[PDB]
Length: 49
Length: 49
Length: 49
Length: 98
Ligand SMILES: CCCCC/C=C/C/C=C/CCCCCCCC(=O)O
Image (cartoon, rainbow over all chains, first blue to last red; front, top):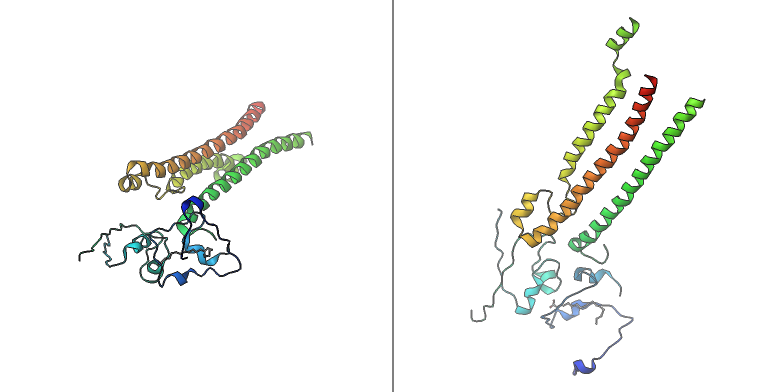
């Protein structure tokens, strides 16, 4: 996104009807923080959400 | 016993992917520790080397 | 098993395994005590016969 | 005379007394064998836990083994207690027959 909401008034986007292929992020995104709470991250590709 | 030292260079935001149970371009395609890994992981910021 | 990786799943599974044995041990103990009672009845029945 | 020779030749009649002995021996041997169970712990051996882990981590592993060991002992006592009720009934009958 060009712009993000401030923490004061955070945005909430609904996601539906799509494939969660997060490997598309590997070519250029970099995340210093990442943690899953309700699922082990290695299982993200075998599940529907 | 059976002591081995694996050794490599990664990006700082990728250090967190070394731990067992993680996902990401390093954990999935370059270097992965087993679920029951019994050793120690050590790392440092070689930004001048 | 679907949501957790092995080392995390193992904790959850071990809690269920212990609990399931607790149910089975309770069952066996109750059957065993009842068996003592039915035997006493059978011995009396044999005596009356 | 026939009883004497019968007892000398075939010991199977005495199986009831042999069974009491064997059952108690097995219960005690079972308690020793169950010591090897991990019960959710990393290792069944306290020395492995204490050598590799510091106190606060070792405490978790030890507590799992302690609970498990009591479970084995409680099982043992309950079985001995039920068997004791049965042996008492036999003893009461034996006293009556005497
Ligand atoms: C907006 C996507 C759809 C939402 C549904 C849930 C999807 C689960 C996926 C989450 C993203 C995981 C990315 C992990 C970081 C990889 C970075 C790298 O290795 O460099």
